Image (cartoon, rainbow over all chains, first blue to last red; front, side, top):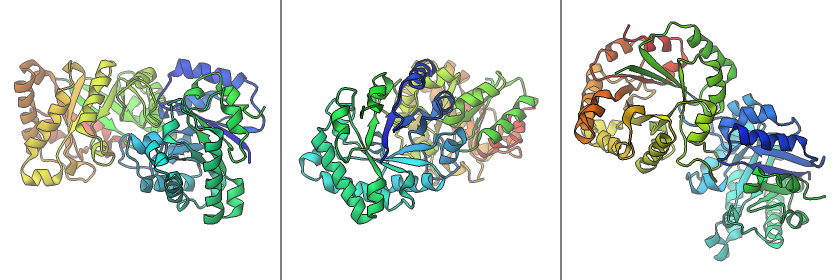
Length: 245
Length: 245
């Protein structure tokens, strides 16, 4: 499984600051073995695709479930492809908990994006009260099934385990907590889908990943990469990409 | 009051078809007495601003309420301005009823966009059930108040009366039902804000406006222009712009 590192810029930047970030990335010594994707604000996807080396992928941070229509404020997979971006992040925690996107909606978006040819980075993760109540497994398998029941071709899917309590809080999961969930998710995949799908699907970890804690998380057997937030806007993003060196 | 015509492209277009539309608008003879604004999909805001003649303004179809932060999928007023866009459409019916944005949130969005120096096109309008119930006034005044409560300076606000039952259905409001609400909204402003605000704020009508309909709508004394959806993607958009000529 090729190591995968996604940087989720979220709602940050302007042309000057993203321009510099991009300059840095195009010049950096990035591992030949890491697949890199930058998640840019919709307003800057064209710019980013124009500026980043072709070796680095571009992802939209969200999309709707039909190619066109009366959905003021939304963008579709067709438009994302039009600009040259090849991925979309769906089901991120902020979409679920701040904007109210349900599993039903997320699963409809995944099927559409995939039908249109985009790769999908599908996020799942439990909240602190769920973790403490001992139902992490129940929650992540329910979120994963909603996605999985809408996936016809797993070759372009990346699963991202983003425990809510860890996003932007500095409270990274320990290597052991991450490994535990990843291993379980891989297991779900083997019995609900197939062994072939289980072995080739990347499951990445997100939630307060830094240049300082990445090497330990990355040595875990079932951690295939990361979905970086806050640190994807900094130069250390380069150290993250190279977490195996 | 300068006649105002805004075209809301909604979730439509690609670089090819939008380039086409923009070339049409750039070569058309548009009335000098009409303020024209095109609301493009976020992904094409930069593109649109770079290709359109300077006399045509560009609007974002939506924005969030803070300058930056952990809001995957959202854009801010600072980003819109970065691109050179001068307006944002907020409170659109699709945002309210498909994406569940509340009056409270819409108000926070207006306050922030205005603080950031953008012009705001704020939408209000009742549903068919409300109209039939005879509570059109109750509903629009409440939505208007939610906006008003967040407007310090009315010089960069355009109120858009967009009855939900008229949006994309083909069921245009009659010239008399549009005038009746506009007049009532203008009176609301007069008594709740000021005579001067009342006199100067443009109140535009949206909901199945066509080249065929526009002239009679535009002749109503309190109808200051239109918010066009479906017809904004056609040649006839030109005729709408020129409705008073």
